[PDB]
Amino acid sequence: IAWIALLLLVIFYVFAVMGTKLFAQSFPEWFGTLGASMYTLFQVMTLESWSMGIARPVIEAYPWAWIYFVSFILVSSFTVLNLFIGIIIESMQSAHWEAEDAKRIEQEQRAHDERLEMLQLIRDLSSKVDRLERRS
Amino acid sequence: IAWIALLLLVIFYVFAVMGTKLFAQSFPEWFGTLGASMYTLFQVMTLESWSMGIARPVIEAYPWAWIYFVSFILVSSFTVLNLFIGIIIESMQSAHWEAEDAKRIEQEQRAHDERLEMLQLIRDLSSKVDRLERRS
Amino acid sequence: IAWIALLLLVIFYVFAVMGTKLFAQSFPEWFGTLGASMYTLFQVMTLESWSMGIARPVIEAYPWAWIYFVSFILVSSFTVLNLFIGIIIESMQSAHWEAEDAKRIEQEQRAHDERLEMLQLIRDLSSKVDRLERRS
Amino acid sequence: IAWIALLLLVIFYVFAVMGTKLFAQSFPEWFGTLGASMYTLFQVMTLESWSMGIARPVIEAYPWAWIYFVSFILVSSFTVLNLFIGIIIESMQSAHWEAEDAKRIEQEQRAHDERLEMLQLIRDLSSKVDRLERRS
């Protein structure tokens, strides 16, 4: 799970220097610094005046900025769906189906211990009886 | 799962040509092209100034545009709920309950192999003994 | 699950006539009709300019409108959390743990059928042998 | 689950007095009272004109207000992810795997009652037979 929090923080970084490279020129409040894109891209990721506020005005300057905003959003929020889920799984299989996966790994092998002892007891009966067709 | 990523990308398309058909006339920044509706309908799907920014001004022109925005959002985001979930299911039944569904398909049939062998061992005891009421 | 899609569409209705009763007076674009509140309340439910756009200007007129917006949002989005989940449950217990809950209801009773037959076979051995302490 | 609804309402409070302390001075519509920050921080939590509306204009006054808004959103919405999930877990383990965890705690011990009775029956056979090598 936290192996993707690394990838997300890589995409956040990658796109932050992308937006600083492109838009630092004409949109210097939003993309002037690396740190100003690291804020704006947190804001665009949270979809708060992402398009009407940032994308639309940036796309008015460069129509090659349409894809940088769409693709950022698709990628960023998608590896959060992969991370949101990475919690539901590691949580629903931990509190619940890691404890059962073990209480049922034990309750199954606690009756191979019964069947396999009961088996021997019938063979020690097969030896006691098949030595009595040979005794009568 | 990805069998609905097709349906979503069909609704996205269907509605993009609907909005270009209707609003290209009077809302040409938003619905002028097919590709301007494919952007606007991504932004309306992301509910970022969806109503106050796009729907409200479009509904001021045509009050038949009220339903095109409500129904788009209901349908679009709903088949994402069917798709978000399509990940939780195929993921929680894959990493967890596809491996257990098989380790417990095997641990069950690994003791029909013990019971059905032990059974025979009692019948070969029933033959040894019922041949001794006939021998005494 | 769909037994709450009724309750949600009741809250949506209840609050729609509440907002038309109160704010139809001074906020007639948003709450003028029942049908204009059924739109605005879909928009406030989708948290798109819900506060800055609708609540803040409505609360400037009446500060008793603060609670109508907060409570609507808490209630509405909460019975969607109860409905979002009503899908994850009915879906994760249907495709996966309704089929297993039955394949393991059968695999369990298919060996009470083995044990309880094996039992008889030992009793018919107990009858054959306890009739041979009485025969020797 | 509701043991974190306390923590969330603590962070909501903690940050409400933080923003009233800092911004009451120059942003008195948003942070003038404790109760005006309790509204603004519900609106910032719902990410409705959170940055462009509140954060951006607050950060223009104080650039130490950048982190108060980012950290608030990260913390607040994150302990809702821990709470959203706290419902999926307590719900998916309740309606489904609390009833199965018990019907399978009983169906397992209802055959230790079969195996352990069948066991004795073979030992009473071992006694009857091992008393007949001593009788012949």
Image (tube, coloured by chain):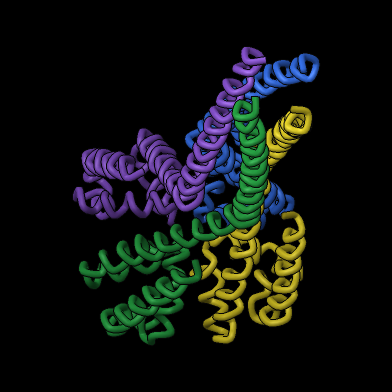
Chain colours: A yellow, B green, C purple, D blue
Residue at x 66% of width, y 55% of height: D59
In depth, the one of D120 and B19 nearer the eye is D120
x then y, percent, for residue B96: 64, 51
**Residue A15 drawn above or below residue D38:** below
x then y, percent, for residue C105: 49, 39
In depth, the one of C71 and A81 nearer the eye is A81
Residue at x 35% of width, y 63% of height: B75
* Residue found farthest to the left: C33
Residue D90, picture quadrant: top right
Whether residue B118 appears in this view of the structure is yes
x then y, percent, for residue A94: 68, 42
From the viewer's perspective, is C10 left or right of C97?
left
**Residue C48 drawn above or below residue D88:** below
Whether residue A110 appears in this view of the structure is no
Residue at x 38% of width, y 87% of height: B33
Residue C59, picture quadrant: top left
Quarter of the image with the C terminus of chain B is top right
In depth, the one of D36 and C92 nearer the eye is C92
Number of marks in picture:
0
x then y, percent, for residue A4: 73, 61
From the viewer's perspective, is B97 left or right of B75?
right
From the viewer's perspective, is D95 left or right of C7?
right
In depth, the one of D75 and B115 nearer the eye is B115
Residue at x 63% of width, y 41% of height: B120
